[PDB]
Length: 394
Ligand code: HEM
Ligand SMILES: Cc1cc(C[C@@H]2NC(=O)[C@H](Cc3ccc(O)cc3)NC2=O)ccc1O
Image 1 (cartoon, protein in one colour):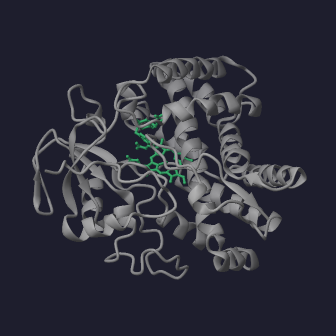
Image 2 (cartoon, rainbow, N blue to C red):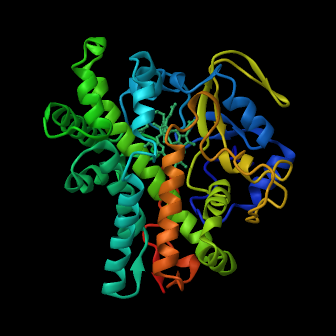
Image 3 (cartoon, protein in one colour):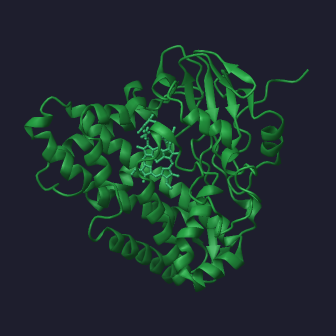
């Protein structure tokens, strides 16, 4: 007697389990059990992942409904699962998306300056260096303080909420509410602070006092700050960290991008495609009976969209484990999702990684792991896959 297949399969972010390819071939939608004990449908082919993400009857909002089968416990108030919907309904979607592009004057230069300063400090201190805690995550934090218009010195405290906020837990987490309420209070004070005039929070502060927004709640304005800081920092920091591993393990690619930095955008797009930073499939709740492959998913059931199932599918990306800079379909991966909930920070996330890699390859052309790859410690029961430390020499 066996048990129902459990998800997630592995917290290791340096390699995909051989098991994913076997599953995609044999059963590209199949029943699994999540850490809560709920049953769910795990979808692992490119075609069926795209189908689910482009059909809004598979709803992200309804995953928050009381009594639903759950992937994990909520770490935000349930109305925040509808965050982008709430922003759109408030008439704020265009302004929010405009504030988080990489295109504001001076933003790219600030990113380069910050990355170079972090790297110079590591070089001064001498190898080994930890590229997660002392490069990728501080670069992500600095970027999001600048994008939000808030003081750089406020970044570390906001950052330290995230090791709990993005937990993937069977049960509610008391610390998550403590930190959430504190971080909301912080952002509410930012909106009242006359010195905050730039970035996303400076723009929201003006719109809040504009008559066209007089009935938008103060709670939503503060929530936009907390959520875009948290999603952006955890996503860019975790992605850059595991991209650095993929790059360091490919010395030929490392040297090519060092020699020809104009290929860095194509390289980052492939690093996005093969990235294992998302620890769980993306969750959706069926709001109707819907045919997905050989399975009739029933109303009220949970569906999990496995991004690396799609992104390593050889029917869409031949030789899927190979980084190839000349693919005919290079941005067609699902690293930023697809459909209604496509990542609103995709351009900024690309530029964060491109600039971080450019700066690293120039400052540390001989970068290499300082420990055997199996010695990395992979964070468990978390919404991202990340090594607790990333020790390198150069
Ligand atoms: C490389 C970096 C990033 C990656 C890999 C990434 C990935 C994703 C993915 C896969 C989704 C879809 C989730 C779903 O459909 O369930 C998403 C949504 C989102 N991302 Fe990103 N993201 C990144 C950077 C950022 C940045 C920089 C921000 C903000 C500054 C951000 C904010 C968000 C938000 C707010 C959503 C939810 C959108 C919605 O529900 O409609 N992300 N991201
Ligand atoms: C835990 C946490 C999540 C967020 C993002 C915020 N929460 C949501 O549930 C929905 C959907 C979602 C999107 C991306 C993601 O990675 C997880 C969920 N949309 C949002 O914008 C922000 C701060 C947090 O502490």
